[PDB]
Image (cartoon, rainbow, N blue to C red; front, top):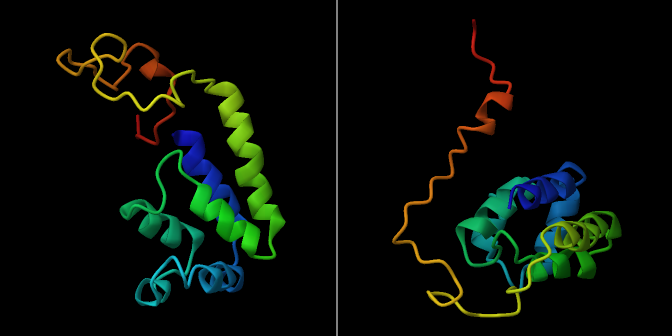
Length: 130
């Protein structure tokens, strides 16, 4: 999920305001013009997209299309290459399986799973004054 954030950020880094409008132009059919006005960045778009059902942490099919229909294979390439690269890392077997709440396979949330890994938390370099 983090790589995905950076992925979008990476193409966003290569995303020009002009290029975005091209994406937006292509997205005129998928994304509303009322929101296109505030899409001054790939981040602004992805954020809107994220805020909406246009872009999940792993769903880039619609965006990858934008990058495809638009004449900017450089951004698409990052998304495309990332798709496989992160997929090659996060080699999930239950990706094709639509099983959600399956205590017989999937793990329930009755157990409290904390995301704060305080074990390897000392490896972070925060800008706090000593």
